[PDB]
Image 1: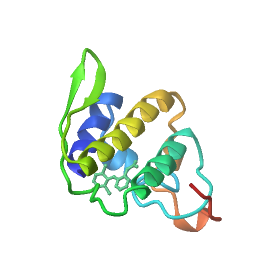
Image 2: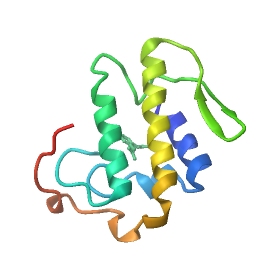
Image 3: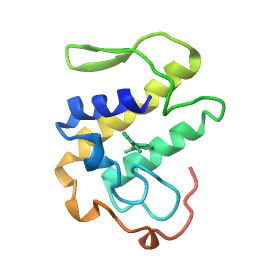
Length: 121
Ligand SMILES: O=C(O)Cc1ccccc1Nc1c(Cl)cccc1Cl
């Protein structure tokens, strides 16, 4: 659930989901359209796509359980949705951590009209 994802984000990046990644680029936080502005934005695009593979699940609200083995993220067994949701978020966190070096504040609160074009998952 959104509640777990943000905590995962924070642990991973030292940054707070809101407002650091809640309105970043064209896909972080609301997704929809356009060309991902950068690596961080790309993580969100993939992440939206990931959630997209689970039409019959509820990513924002279904809670899952996970643990850290030394500093690794390990999703604990739950319902199938729960397991695939977790794998989706885990990927996004690692991705964020992997591009923190190019995170740019000029993409915070990015305006909608500056996101043109569809991109397929
Ligand atoms: O992919 C992301 O960076 C995050 C993301 C994607 C889809 C929907 C919500 C969020 N984030 C989000 C979070 Cl992480 C907390 C509170 C409110 C919102 Cl809208």
